[PDB]
Amino acid sequence: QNTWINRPEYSEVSEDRIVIVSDANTDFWENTYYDFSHYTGHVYGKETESDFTFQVRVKADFSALYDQAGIFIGGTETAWIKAGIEFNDGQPSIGCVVTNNNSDWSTGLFPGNPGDFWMRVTSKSDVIRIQYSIDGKNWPLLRLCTWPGTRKRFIGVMCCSPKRKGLSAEFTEILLTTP
Amino acid sequence: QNTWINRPEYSEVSEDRIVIVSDANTDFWENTYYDFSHYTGHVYGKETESDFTFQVRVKADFSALYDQAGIFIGGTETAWIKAGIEFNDGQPSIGCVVTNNNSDWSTGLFPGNPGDFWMRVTSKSDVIRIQYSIDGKNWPLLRLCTWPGTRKRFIGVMCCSPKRKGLSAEFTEILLTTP
């Protein structure tokens, strides 16, 4: 059954729609460079011990620095992966952070509509393939690595407000299935 | 003193210019997904045990699938990092691969001129910050992680031809210095 990691004050959970409103100063980051350990981001999903392909359509109102919305894959508090859009110096970026004791993040240009995009995560064997889409048809690769956690993987939708509060993210067309 | 990792058949080494012509089927990759271990890419540089900032201007004639040219940071054969342009399905991408026993790669859109760009690597403490530039003035972030190797880091220019032979890459404006 679906459950939360840092359940937010405000939210909505329907059969085919999930809304996460971030709490103040929420984020996910481990040590690397910044020297702090944040594990306060919001994630709604479920644990699974089998391979899978997760896909979701994200609609959030990015505005404050470091606003994040996308997907999350958890193992432990020091073994997880997050990916999606992140606001910074205006322009929106698409990136990913793989944390295996330490956070390793990559980022880059996001061409689509920052307020309406798709995310896809495929986890078969010990491999993690993360892709995104701006039209729901084309899925460019974002990150390809090997899972840093164990058997149990927590897969779900995520939302972060490192410098603010209230980022509202709507998740629809959610589909968790065999790879 | 400067030395090679998989010295190529053809090359040129001047005081302020380095040309690497790739040998057939050369590449850098460790296990993840593809299930093969490649350590045949060409790298010209030097070992250092102190923090540094490396910068270089790259001019290569990308054409065959997976053609790569950029920078490399080595620790061991299972602990290294590479970053730069990579040709694929025509369009050129800017990406990075961090290998800590297993390769973890990120990729994305490259807006500049694929045949003339800059790379910058900063290694202070145990942090690695990789940036690129399309005009030699602006340096967007590409990857930020913590070094997977030890004290001795091999920093230098790199060139790969996974599916061909002959990719000629020219490296100029090389500058290795304190961060």
Image: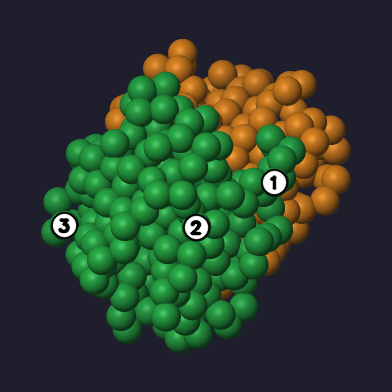
Chain colours: A green, B orange
The disc numbered 1 marks a residue on which chain?
A: A
Q: Write the residue at 21% across / 45% down.
A: A116
The local crowd at label 2, few if under 14, some if 14 to 19, many if 20 or more residues have their Cα within 10 Å, is some
Q: Amino acid at mark 1?
A: Ser
Question: In this rendering, does residue A5 appear at all?
Answer: yes
Q: Write the residue at 25% across / 47% down.
A: A59
Compared to B27, does B169 lie above or below? above
In the displayed structure image, the side of residue A99 where residue A7 appears, left or right: left
Helix or strand or loop: what does disc 2 sit on? loop
- Residue labelled with disc 1: A37
* Count of numbered labels shown in the rendering: 3
Q: CA distance from mark 2 to mark 3?
A: 28 Å
Measured as percent of width and height from the top left, residue B32 is found at: 52, 70
The disc numbered 2 marks a residue on which chain?
A: A
- Residue labelled with disc 2: A7
In the displayed structure image, the side of residue B44 where residue B110 appears, left or right: left
Measured as percent of width and height from the top left, residue A130 is found at: 39, 61
In the displayed structure image, the side of residue A58 where residue B142 appears, left or right: right
The disc numbered 3 marks a residue on which chain?
A: A
